[PDB]
Image (spheres, coloured by chain):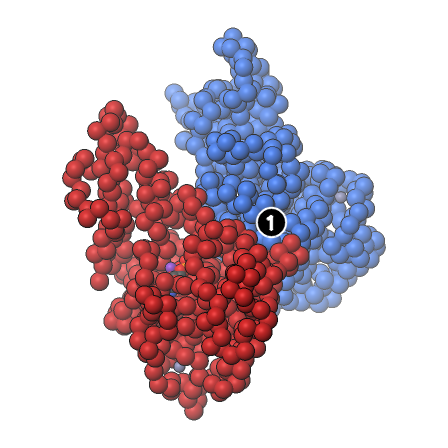
Chain colours: A red, B blue
Amino acid sequence: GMSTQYWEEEIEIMSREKLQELQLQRLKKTINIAANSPYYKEVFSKNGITGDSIQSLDDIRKIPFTTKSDMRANYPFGLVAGDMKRDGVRIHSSSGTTGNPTVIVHSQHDLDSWANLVARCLYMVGIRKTDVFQNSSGYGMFTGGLGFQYGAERLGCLTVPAAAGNSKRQIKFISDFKTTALHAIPSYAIRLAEVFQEEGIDPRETTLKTLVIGAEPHTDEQRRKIERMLNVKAYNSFGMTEMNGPGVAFECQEQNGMHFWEDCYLVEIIDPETGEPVPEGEIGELVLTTLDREMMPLIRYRTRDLTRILPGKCPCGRTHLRIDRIKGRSDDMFIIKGVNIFPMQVEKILVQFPELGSNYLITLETVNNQDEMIVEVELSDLSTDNYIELEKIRRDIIRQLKDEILVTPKVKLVKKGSLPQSEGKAVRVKDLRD
Amino acid sequence: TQYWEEEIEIMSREKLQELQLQRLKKTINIAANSPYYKEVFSKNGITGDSIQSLDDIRKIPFTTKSDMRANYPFGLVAGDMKRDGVRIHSSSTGNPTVIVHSQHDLDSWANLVARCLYMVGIRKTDVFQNSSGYGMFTGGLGFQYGAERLGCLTVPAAAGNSKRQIKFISDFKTTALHAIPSYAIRLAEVFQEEGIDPRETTLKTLVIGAEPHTDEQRRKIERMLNVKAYNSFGMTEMNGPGVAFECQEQNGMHFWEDCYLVEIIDPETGEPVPEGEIGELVLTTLDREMMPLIRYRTRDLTRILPGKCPCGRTHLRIDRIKGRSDDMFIIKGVNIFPMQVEKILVQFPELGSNYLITLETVNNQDEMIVEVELSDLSTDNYIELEKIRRDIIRQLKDEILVTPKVKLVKKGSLPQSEGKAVRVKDLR
Ligand SMILES: Nc1ncnc2c1ncn2[C@@H]1O[C@H](COP(=O)(O)OP(=O)(O)O)[C@@H](O)[C@H]1O
Ligand SMILES: Nc1ncnc2c1ncn2[C@@H]1O[C@H](COP(=O)(O)OP(=O)(O)O)[C@@H](O)[C@H]1O
Ligand SMILES: [K+]
Ligand SMILES: [K+]
Ligand SMILES: [K+]
Ligand SMILES: [Zn+2]
Ligand SMILES: [Zn+2]
């Protein structure tokens, strides 16, 4: 607190009263912009939302929630409010070809606001322009790639856009370029420490000092295990494509709850049953409204993430609220290797193969500290194929699943009737991870 | 014509040489701070007064790939990397080359890419899709920063997943696409597989590079997708994309002489070739500060196309890159380039674009086999296709001065590489 350094001091230690004043000003601006989108223009017309409906921050509960289903219904540009042809500079899309994915469109302002938030996060945990920042996140459509790339360049780091995979190349970059800061998912940070030992390098004696980990749920003990393996300080990083990507919520150097940047997001913790705010400090669904987005703002978006607001002031001096770890979700979505997957994406691929039966089972396991996804599917006794032909089909199933869910799964063709008789519900994901 | 930077793109040759000399002296003074060029300049008596004319650059020795491997990773870094270094890129072997950029270097690079896209008619109203690999490879971030700088609605699709590439083009109404020539053909084939006419999409402009390709292969891509395709040159050492680029005349690639000093040197003598002859492309960065490169031997073989261009731009044009020095192979003591084989295969419409040259040793003698896929448009029978196969062997024996074995294979039988297509497989 007495010796804490801030990227934007005036905003990061802003009084709660002036912070709420800033939220209300940006909330009115966001509602007036979103009114230009075809989607929110209909929502505001149906629910009588005018430019005078929002007079306080509590007036936001007048607006209905925006769901993933509504965004799929208005795919691809139903929620675009700005001039996409003149001001639109980027699209970020979620995985899939069997269904309508999620699309977020950004203007140059939106990219700058997003890069500033990521720079604010990196600076908060002690990362400076003198640091060598390596990003092991996937690039392309994944917001983790370009998100940290623009943020680290904005801070002034010597960036190493390593991208995903190739552990031996990740270790080569750290050794040759003297990397000090690394962005990786918790499970891959353990893999890199393992590969360091395989190549005869002490993972505790590298140039690494700071680690940024997120994208998937992990315990505080898992993080402390990563800190001991690599002799580093690891910080929890939260974000999602709908909210830009990285830079949404981030731990401070106290490593106790993730500070949510309330100047760019309005945070609500909602009871998934009633749809009403939970008692202060209880676990509920995270519902978010963008406050600095102009091309495609999102109002009261149901993340389906479950968390709580941690009570008490933080010793770092920052007044922005802190959320607890995200330990689960209120929908059927699962995360493997940091990638979000829906079970229907797997089913929509399997049904295309007449050699397969309708009964399938997706099992998630931890092997050698790395996450593995196994897809068991029964064979239809209609299959008039031998071993060589069925094995060629199995490889095609792996290929079509890899293209759809963006992770390589293990496909096992099992005998008809071998898989256990389900309760008759769509619950077909058996997670066996700790 | 419409220009991104009119004052520079149609600048008089006299003022363009004046600009080159000013930036050449600056580059030499900056590079003198690097451990590598500090030794090179001291050994060769290169001072701040050695360069008085653009011809005085021939006082400085060449920088090779071997020199960069020897000084890997930061032996040629001239600026303050800890303070001002904002990115490291790696080329696509042994230890890959490393180029370190400052914020100035990234801005100069992004500006050159936006200048290129604007030259071929791409505007902020276009939807730009980049199918280049994203990460250490300069094609990803290089075209991303350029297209955003111009103001395009960018689609960072990255490499692979053809079904997803086609979905983005259909749903986001993509108008401009960056792809390697071989992948542009793959996308057109996948369009047909998914029941979409590849000639009836929102695509208007294509940017193709990385792979050496013939003009006829480019015209084939233009007919498949009903687009205008433009040749894009670049390399990690020279930033990446935005180095050289065709104009709307599609006749030679304009080299941006405000950021690069171009030399065509004879690999034997080490002297400049007679004006317009084929030699090794030797390049010097003019607007790089963190890690400038002086007289770098690219290993690329090309020539400077003579005459001014009808587009009005005064920047010189290079011909297509016939091939790299490492791409060349030796069979029966005869030097042969893979592009010599491709230039003959493309003039047969019965053949596909996918081919593979395999080199083997049979009975202590070297043998050269050329596998080439048949196009689905071939309505010819056995006797007619065999007459074509004999004509292919004949025109090849006359071109490469060696008799090869030509085998017409089924469409899709030859392997497709993830990145650049592999045209030569040496098994000796
Ligand atoms: N730090 C984190 N801890 C737990 N879950 C996280 C964390 N960061 C992200 N997630 C999960 O990932 C989701 C965001 O996924 P996504 O939009 O695909 O972005 P990304 O490319 O980073 O995975 C969140 O809604 C949440 O469920
Ligand atoms: N337009 C082009 N036509 C032919 N060859 C090209 C072209 N662009 C690049 N190349 C080749 O690729 C080399 C650069 O490769 P590299 O630095 O690894 O970049 P990249 O990631 O795009 O492959 C050049 O030296 C040249 O041999
Ligand atoms: K730096
Ligand atoms: K995730
Ligand atoms: K645009
Ligand atoms: Zn704090
Ligand atoms: Zn021209």
Query: Looking at the image, which residue is at 35% across and 51% down?
Result: A342
Query: Looking at the image, which residue is at 57% across and 56% down?
Result: A38
Is B370 situated left or right of B49 in this image?
left
Q: Chain of mark 1?
A: B
> In which quadrant is the C terminus of chain B drawn?
top left
Residue A230 locus on image (x, y percent): 31, 69
Which quarter of the figure has residue A365? bottom left
Residue A189 locus on image (x, y percent): 33, 63
Is A144 situated left or right of B285 in this image?
left
Considering the numbered disc 1 on the image, is that residue within a helix, a strand or a loop? strand
- Image vertical order of residue A398 relative to residue A342, above or below: above
Name the residue carrying label 1: B128
Q: Which amino acid does the dot numbered 1 rest on?
A: Phe
User: Which residue appears farthest toward the bottom when viewing the image?
Assistant: A2
Residue A196 locus on image (x, y percent): 31, 61
Residue A275 locus on image (x, y percent): 37, 67
Question: Is residue B289 something one can see in this rendering?
Answer: no
Q: In front: B414, or A411?
A: A411
Q: In front: A233, or A237?
A: A237
Q: In front: A69, or A8?
A: A69
Query: Looking at the image, which residue is at 65% across and 40% down?
Result: B204
